[PDB]
Every structure is written in structure tokens, then in C-alpha cells.
Image (cartoon, helix red, strand yellow):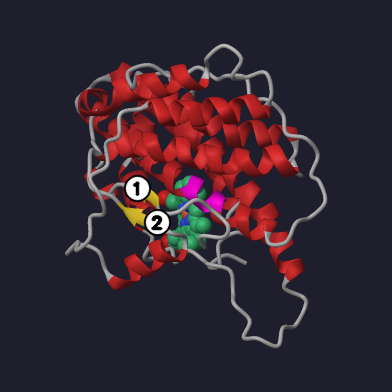
Amino acid sequence: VAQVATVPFRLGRPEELPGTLDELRAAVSARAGEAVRGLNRPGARTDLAALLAATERTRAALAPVGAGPVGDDPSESEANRDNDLAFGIVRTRGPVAELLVDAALAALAGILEVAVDRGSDLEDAAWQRFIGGFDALLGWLADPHSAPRPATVPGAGPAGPPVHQDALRRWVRGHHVFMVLAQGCALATACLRDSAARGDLPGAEASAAAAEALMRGCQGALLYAGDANREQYNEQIRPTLMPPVAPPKMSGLHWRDHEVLIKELAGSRDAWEWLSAQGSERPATFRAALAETYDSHIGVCGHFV
Ligand code: HEC
């Protein structure tokens, strides 16, 4: 795993994520705002290489917040740990939402490193959706009471000649993006539920806008991982004399960030209907995004056809 992605990939415990807009703003908006400003600095968006350099410069300029590994976590099953280990994930002590900002910037850099060198085979609209998911996450975290504004995403060159195990690199780095987006969407959905419960219609609307933008980013990430997985299957046609090692795979049951996201989404049904009744257009477009993300599990998740 260390030969295919920068690890440890440090992430907080998703069970600790804030659950209200005011709590989220207090926890992360300062640091997210710094991240957004770094990624939108003069020259950062001229081309993909500039965005990569801006991402690494932004990461370096941020105050470190981690306090080392969580270590012994009574809430973490062995199967949770195995799921994390398979992708080089280390659950890290510290402010969970600030660690999410760090993880988002690191996952972005991981994606851009490969794309700057080897291009991408993704359709330009999928590339825009995928990378745009980072702008949605960080822009929303910078000001959770407002919908986030989309930004320019430089295009990726056409895919170059295959290098050994590049598909595995994209597979693993893509899953690092999954974990960031799952936490982000869990945050947005929790804030939607809380705002609706408290009758905060503007807060529900902003949270729903974030949830949909993050859901579209997740769909783009699933397309990116599906492209990597298909290439992986082709590299697997060769029989090997050494024991054949399967690519790492997420469990579903034992992937904590996804479990937290799904539980939030389940409890949000009434908030989505209430937004509809209050004149929002977000429920209908979120429903479309949700359907597309679900269908795009096919060819990525081992528990789908
Ligand atoms: C395989 C492990 C994956 C990975 C790589 C992703 N998810 Fe997804 N997901 C998975 C399963 C087994 C299910 C269905 C569980 C069941 O059958 O009961 C889902 C479903 C979802 C849904 C729908 C939830 C709902 O309808 O309430 C969503 C929204 C979802 N998953 C999100 C999601 C995202 C955003 C992912 C990448 C960032 C992602 N999943 C990956 C299993 C898997």
C-alpha cells in the first residue's frame, strides 16, 4: 500500500463529527477558509500542475492539528481496523472536522499527482464533478450557513501510456477520496436534519445544497474508481506463479465513514420532504444525484454486480 499512495492517510473518527451548523462553523470554518483561499490563490487554477503546487503549498501552510493515532478504540471492531488497514488509513486524534480539512487536501494532492503525470481517461464532465467535490466540501465548511459556489477545475490531459500498477494507485487514492466525501456528506446531512428539526429553513437549505454537491462529487469519485477497477481487472488476466494478491476492497458493513453517512441519510427523509413543501428545488436534484451515485456503485463495490 505504501508503494501506491502516501500513507498513513490520517482521518478522524466519523462518530465524532459535529451535528449542527453552529457547531460545525465553530469547529472548522477558520481552517476551511484558509484551505479555500490557498486553493484559489493567484495562479492556482491555470492548469493542473499549478493546482497541485497550490494544494501542497496550502497543506504546508496550515497549523498542524493531529495528535497521533487513536490507537486503542473500544468502539472499533477488528473488522473496522482491517477495513482501514487495507487502504493505509490511520484514525487520528484531534479535532475531527479540522482533520477532515487536512485529509481533503491530502486526498486531492494524491489524485492530482497521478493526473499531472499520466492524465486521465475520464470524461471532462466527470472530471469536473469529481475534482469539484473538493471545492464543494471546503467551500461549504468555510461557511456552512451558505450554499457553496462552484469553481473552475483545470482539465486533465489525455491518459498516457500505462505504468505498472497505476490502476491500483488510482484505486487506492480514489478510496481516500471516498472517505473524505463520506464524512463531508454525513456532516451536511446531519446539519440538514438538525436545522429542519429546529425550523431553520435557511440552514436546512444550505445543508441540502452541500449534501447534493457532495453527492455529485461522490458520483464522480465512483466513476474515477470504476475506471481504475476496470483497468485493474485487465492487469489481473495474467496468471502468476506467486499467490495472486487481490486489490484491497472496502467491506461495507465494516467501513465506519460509510456506516455513519448511511445512518444520517436514513434519518433525513422527512427533512427532504419538508424542504420540498417549503419551495426548495434541492430535494429533486438531490434525489437525482442520489440515484446516480447508487447506480455508480456497480463496478466499484464488491457487494454490487
Ligand atoms: C462497497 C464497499 C461500497 C463502496 C465503495 C461505497 N459504498 Fe455506498 N453502499 C454500499 C452498500 C453495500 C450499500 C447498500 C446497503 C444495503 O444494501 O442495505 C450502499 C448504499 C449507498 C447509498 C444509499 C443509501 C440509502 O439509500 O439510504 C449511498 C447514498 C451511498 N452508498 C454512498 C456512497 C458513497 C457516497 C460512496 C463513495 C464516496 C460509496 N457509497 C461507496 C457499499 C459501498
Pointer 1 residue: 11
Considering every residue shown, the one lying at the far left of the view is: 74
> Residue at horizontal 61%, vertical 38%?
112
In contact (CB < 8 Å): disc 1 and disc 2: yes
Q: Quadrant of residue 74?
A: bottom left
Q: Secondary structure at mark 2?
A: strand
Please name the predominant secondary structure of the magenta segment in the image.
Answer: helix
Residue stretch in magenta: 173-178
Residue 278 as seen in the image, left or right of residue 213: left
Mark 2 surroundings within 10 Å by alpha-carbon count, few (fewer than 14), some (14 through 19), many (20 or more): some
Q: Earlier in the sequence, mark 1 or mark 2?
A: 1
Asked if the stretch drawn in magenta spans residue 139, the answer is no
Tell me where residue 87 appears, x and y as whole percent. 47, 60
Q: Quadrant of residue 292?
A: top right
> Residue at horizontal 70%, vertical 32%?
125
Name the disc covering residue 89, or none.
Answer: 2
Tell me where residue 49 appears, x and y as whole percent. 66, 29
